[PDB]
Image (cartoon, rainbow, N blue to C red):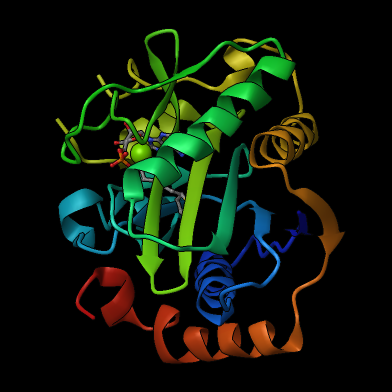
Length: 247
Ligand SMILES: [N]C1=N[C]=NC2=C1N=[C]N2[C]1O[C]([C]OP([O])(=O)/O=C(\[O])[C][C][C][C][C]2[C][C]SS2)[C]([O])[C]1[O]
Ligand SMILES: [Mg+2]
C-alpha cells in the first residue's frame, strides 16, 4: 500500500526525460513499490511509437521556434509540451493484459483529483486511436480536451503516462501539430480554474493515492534506474533514427 513519488524532471532535455520514463518502467519488477512520477518538458513535440515525425509535425516551425522533437516508447498520437504542461507516469505490478482497466482506473483518479480543484472533467467516449479527442484515453472538461494518455504492458508490469494542459500556449500547440480547429478542441485547466502546476500536481497525488489506495511518499530514482536511463538515452533517445521514428 506504499509507493514512490518521483519528482524526476529534466526540462531542457525531453529525450533524457523520456529515457527516465522507460527506465523506471523497464527496471520495475513484479512486487516493487508502485511508482508515480511528475515531470515537465520545455517547448517540445512528442510523437507516438508508431509515428513518423515528418507526418505529424513541421520540421521547420520547430526548427525556427526551437521546439525539441522526441518520440516516446508508447503508442498514441502527437502532442505539444511546454512548462505549462504537466506530465505524469504510473508504473505498477501487473497480473493481466487488460489495457482498458488501466486507463479506466487512472482516469477515475484524474477525475477525483481535478474535482478537488473545482474542475469537473470526464473521460472521452470513443474507441478510435486515430481521432484527436473524445477517446476513452482522453480527459475532457466541457467540450474541450485537457489531457491525453498512453500506456504499455509487459509480463509483470504496466505503464500509463499522460500530458495535462495547465497553462500551455495552446496557439503554439495548434500551429505545430499537423492534423486536419485544433485550437478549438483543446483547453488549459487554468481556462477553468486559477491553480498552479504545484496545486495540480498536489491534487493528482491525492487523487491517485485515494483511488489506488497507495501512500505515495516522495522518493528518488535509484542508481540502477538512473543507469538504465543513461543507457537508453545514449543508445536510443539521443539518436535521430529513433526520434524521427525509424528505429
Ligand atoms: N499536451 C497535450 N495534452 C492534451 N492534449 C494535447 C496536448 N498536445 C496536443 N493535444 C491535443 O491532443 C491530440 C492528440 O491525440 P492523441 O492521439 O490522444 O495523443 C495523446 O494524448 C498522447 C498522450 C501523450 C502522453 C504524454 C506525452 C509524453 S510521455 S506522457 C492532438 O492533436 C491535440 O488536439
Ligand atoms: Mg489520449
